[PDB]
Amino acid sequence: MEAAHSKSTEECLAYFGVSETTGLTPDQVKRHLEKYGHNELPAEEGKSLWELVIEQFEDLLVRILLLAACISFVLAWFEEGEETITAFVEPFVILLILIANAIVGVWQERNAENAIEALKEYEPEMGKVYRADRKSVQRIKARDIVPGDIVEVAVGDKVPADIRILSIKSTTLRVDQSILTGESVSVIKHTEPVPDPRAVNQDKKNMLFSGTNIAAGKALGIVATTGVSTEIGKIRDQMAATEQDKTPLQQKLDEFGEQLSKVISLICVAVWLINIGHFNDPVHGGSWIRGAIYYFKIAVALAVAAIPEGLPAVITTCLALGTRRMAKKNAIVRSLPSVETLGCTSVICSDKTGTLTTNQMSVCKMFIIDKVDGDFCSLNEFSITGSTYAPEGEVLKNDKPIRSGQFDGLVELATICALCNDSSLDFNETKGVYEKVGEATETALTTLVEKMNVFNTEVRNLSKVERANACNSVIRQLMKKEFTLEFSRDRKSMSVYCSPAKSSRAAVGNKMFVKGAPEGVIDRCNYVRVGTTRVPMTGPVKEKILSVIKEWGTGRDTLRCLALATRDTPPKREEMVLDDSSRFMEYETDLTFVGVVGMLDPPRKEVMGSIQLCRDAGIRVIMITGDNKGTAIAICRRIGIFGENEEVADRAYTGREFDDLPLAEQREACRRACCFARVEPSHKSKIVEYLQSYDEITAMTGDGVNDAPALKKAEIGIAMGSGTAVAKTASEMVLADDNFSTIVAAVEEGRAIYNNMKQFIRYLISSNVGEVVCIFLTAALGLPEALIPVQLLWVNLVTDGLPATALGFNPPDLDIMDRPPRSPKEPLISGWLFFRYMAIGGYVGAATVGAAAWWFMYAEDGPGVTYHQLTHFMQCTEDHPHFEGLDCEIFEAPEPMTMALSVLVTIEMCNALNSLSENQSLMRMPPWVNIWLLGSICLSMSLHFLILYVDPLPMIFKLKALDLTQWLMVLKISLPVIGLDEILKFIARNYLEG
Ligand SMILES: Nc1ncnc2c1ncn2[C@@H]1O[C@H](COP(=O)(O)OP(=O)(O)O)[C@@H](O)[C@H]1O
Ligand SMILES: CC(=O)C1=C(O)N2[C@H](C1=O)[C@H]1c3c[nH]c4cccc(c34)C[C@H]1C2(C)C
Ligand SMILES: [Mg+2]
């Protein structure tokens, strides 16, 4: 049953053909349960760390390194015999690494709880129904409740499904819809039909939402809807249908994988296009099976040479070192990768209260009527001092303390403020400061009537706790509060019925004390109180009163105002239908305006500047809020969302305004919009959506399951420390302190973490372009492979591994925040940056081939046969060009391999320095700025040395320590790269700029 709130109580029974007294027949419970299904949310879709690992191996590159592991096996030999112990490492090291890389994409790549799974913690187990096949209140599994059947809720219950209230058995009924909203204060319910078919949840005051708690009272009602069809069930369903996109990194990293997988099997057919000459060899001679086996050593070599295998380990380290770093600045980031996407944040929508402002509301201007004669309408207006809830501060007229109670009207102003108030102060003994109890707005009122002190109650001889609510009390002695008519968005006010108590003066009857939004309250006064007299409300009087409320609210004070009026002669106690919330506004009529108080909710000292920081960072801030559009805008100026004078006509919208536009101009309104006043949570989704239709990366605050759907949709959902459970689960980032500037900080950190990533990502790659171009020479010119698998793995995992990581501690630009947000269409390698890493890659693919074969050519202690056609023969089936002598097998010597390896490692340690900045010379950007890059190189070399003289290692790497003459040739052929680099830096600096 869909629009239940809008049907009469009988209409709802007539709809399910059920008797409020008896309940659902055990037949109906059958047919129904068939029509509607069970009162549960669909079961989890499932996961598992075994199919999670299997999912990682389906990737293209991890398909290749696993193919190279297959070939690494079909290269050696068959099944068991005896021992040449040393051998099978090359296929076992990769298979080790892959498992230790799949694993790293999981148990520190958190992929676990979702805000959708959280929504199975506010669906209850047990509910209480009245079916026909008993007579007592049979408690059943919530899961088995179903539309139509009668239900019983009492204080402390979790509401089991969405329920149209039938009758309230207790005095009143108070529900706690925190989960949806977040606003501790419970709400009153009634049974009248809310007759508008499309009423928001805030206004469905005869309904209980599944997941809510009864906070007082006890009622019986009929289930309107269950399962996915309840209000919380529908929020579940929106988050279900959300397509969750990958980050701008994992997206362009994935098309790097595809580009790398395409290049490998393009070189593995390009090497073939150069060995096509083998078709001209004799049918007899050389090794058939052997022919096949060769091409498979270079394939495997080409596999490992273009990977960068460390990458994963490095990234993960870098991100996990970012999380710990943002947590210090109060940003809890939950999703790992979120830290990179945090860096392209284009737009930030923040809630006002609590994030932009401190929710420390206090009154600080107020006025009453002074005198009224024809047109002259003079006001009598004061100011209050004190930002806190503490009863410390003073009232001043004409900028100078006055004793509040000498003004008759100020008495009334305080009387209403105290009696028409549902909140209160408390002194906290621990912190040593006052506490609000209830609404912030109301508690501010309670603090006022304290500062005011209209009766001159002795207050300085009281104690911190006793005095908090002192004068309020005195006033609660004066009038007795019978009943009270709660607030409703609908009439925008609230009022309490009061009768006098002891030997007072009031008499002849009692009064209603109304307190609500202006116009609302003012449009309902026929009389104005001037002093203790009263006179009829006139145009000129009204126009004053409004002119000032407008000035205060829309001024540079940005005050929120309340009108305070009284019904001097109220309806008879037995004339008002107190269950009929719809009729509350008529009882609040024919009021007498008493006066207006205006309060403030100060913007965080921090935010002002933070906002500016985003201006310069090129990122847009949108402030969502609940103030009226006028004051909404005025707060925007004050925090500098807008300039103090500038146009804003089509830049701020309200809830209703925004709804009145057809989609095209809603979509439009979103790229220029900065401020939304009085919005539905419904809109937060629509706004995120629209912002994305503009490829904006959107940070979005919100709390309560109401805002869960948009914290999901937003690239960066942001919950609050103080927030609800579910909201947090829906976000990717949580402000431990709720501060808006905590967002801004985190976006800058994320800006820096991505910048440093762009670096070491290109560094680790820079090697792989070299390592290949090396093995392309050692194959294209037919020498002996200067580098093999088990060497390269060490370089990519460990040799470059420590320096790449240490490049994640680089000192961030001093204009890191003074440049526009980086696009999500930026490629990590492009323009002059491609030809700079095809040079450095084309230089390493030469220097590792030069100095190694140089041991086969120009060496002293090595067989130095210059131009000995190493290209012609590595078969030695002939042994004709080498007449006398008996030794071929020196082509598998450890020393030449050790020449290439020492060239690489050292160039890498050079190129690591070349990364510390993109276009600053090592002259301008000193190598000793990153103390952790120097520290890493240090540890990198002392590993190149370790694997050379601790004998097990150099035997396994197939190496042997080079002589001191074989150490200088390295530095002769290695260092020159820092020189090729600098030339490129000062060029892109000085002829590729403009
Ligand atoms: N859509 C609306 N229509 C009318 N008034 C509203 C609406 N949204 C909120 N308000 C009022 O605005 C007041 C201030 O909202 P605010 O403190 O911004 O809310 P929030 O917790 O969303 O920040 C709320 O107390 C509520 O009384
Ligand atoms: C077993 C496992 O899950 C993984 C891995 O073990 N790896 C990565 C990978 O995801 C591989 C990969 C996929 N896409 C890219 C882009 C850039 C770099 C890499 C990759 C490294 C790859 C490898 C094999 C190290
Ligand atoms: Mg809020």
Image: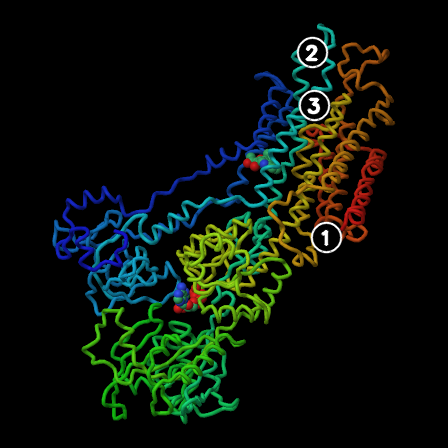
Would you say the residues marked 3 and 1 are in contact, meaning their CB atoms lie under 8 Å apart? no
The image shows residue 316, relative to residue 257, as above or below, that is below
In the image, which disc is placed on residue 931? Answer: 1
Residue 20 in sight in this render: yes
Say few, some or many: other residues with alpha carbon within 10 Å of mark 3 (under 14 / 14 to 19 / 20 or more).
some
Q: Which mark is residue 287?
A: 2
Q: What's the distance in space between the residues labelled 3 and 1, CA to CA?
A: 43 Å
Q: Amino acid at mark 2?
A: Ser
Q: Position of residue 750 (x, y in %)?
A: 60, 53
Q: Is residue 513 left or right of residue 606?
A: left
Q: Quadrant of residue 778?
A: top right
Residue assigned mark 3: 270
Per the image, label 3 sits on a secondary structure element best described as loop
Give the SS element for disc 1: helix
Q: In the rendered structure, which amino acid carries the disc numbered 1?
A: Ile
Q: Residue at x 57, y 41 (%)?
A: 251
Q: Is residue 240 above or below residue 79?
A: below
Which numbered disc, 1 or 2, marks the residue that appears first in the sequence? 2
